[PDB]
Image (tube, rainbow over all chains, first blue to last red; front, side, top):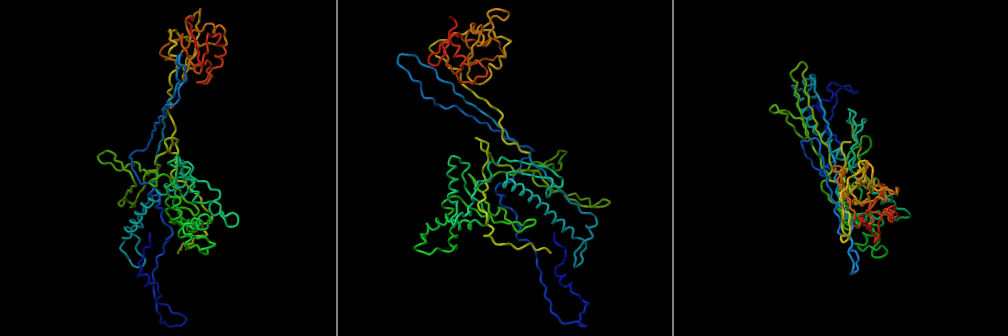
Length: 409
Length: 145
């Protein structure tokens, strides 16, 4: 929604034509005009978790999973001891066993509407010039595009709610829940937070820190050599990760080793330029995992500009970097075709033109049905660990530049 | 709450049958079962189990088998054998009682409150007057004699 004005016609019109000043005659002057367009550059859309699962359709309303597990008996049990002139002895009884399990699924629902009454359909034009009542065809077509952006925003909110907590929680006192509904949807995410009581920039004592991240993320790979779904593969971090590594006094000795920087001889100790410029590659080579930086930002309701992945926090992936999950579109009643009801999945957009009745109007309804769904649990013990969250430092904000406040006319 | 996580439904355990000495020999006769005995909790469980049966020598239920009351000296004096790996008690009421075999001591429990695969100490204690002979951790019995 922009203001319906004419730009050039309004600059040439906010100029008093019949006004004189304290000098009681009209005076000479020179006038320059300029046009500015104020936007918020630092409120971007969380397009990270769009790739962490694609979208799918099912034309059903519930999905159920069945798992059948078998456990045979082992060929163990050494042999019984004999003497030559006697009889044999019988062998013990073994046991085999099978179990079977079940899980379900069912989606959510959301739709909304908007209506335009009879006055504003033909009683609005521009503000500088005059227009023969056709600005509503411009303003509906933006609001038609806006309703598609609502559902794309609603999909990402549920998606990030799983990615951050593994818990869809909807409360009545909530933005964009006027109907006052209740959902607490607990997915089966096991141990979403990695423990780290001294983070990386604790720096207890004089100047020496406490925890080596090259050793910490190598400790995790060592403790999951026989847990193949549990060793880390990549890490996605916010902006200020190199500035934690460069002030660490453990990682620094890795940087000095690969360049021969003994401080007492050979060199005076360098500044933090190259001492941080090589902090990524020495982290990537000695932990073996990938690092992706996601510094994309949004603006808070009240405060300053925040990051999507928060400041002193990162995510840790596991056995694959591929799609962790799936977003499912379920069925919805579309229009009939030949007396039979026809269905459809995905976001829909229905037009209800009542432009010929006694007060005419025009209405649009938009929504869909669906919910995210995780990929697949561990069959042995029913656990899910593909992503985990780590709070790695406390004072990353002091290593980050500030932001412009939101300009508001 | 719109998603149920995995929970198990079926629980099937398939054990093997009660082993016995090949060279000692078999002798088994089918007897009728006592209807007053709740035979459900005697054949309950997937575990390999044997148990002793007595017989009513007289009265209105004569010739019917019932599990041996070890606290009764009359039921100890009337033991006739063991039931090995119990049958369909619901479709039929005539059990095959083994009168002569050689069974390890880990597979014979009298009490329902007795763990499987463990020796029943009440059976070992009364094995002199139950005509049981414990040799090499095995019960030897023959009730034809």
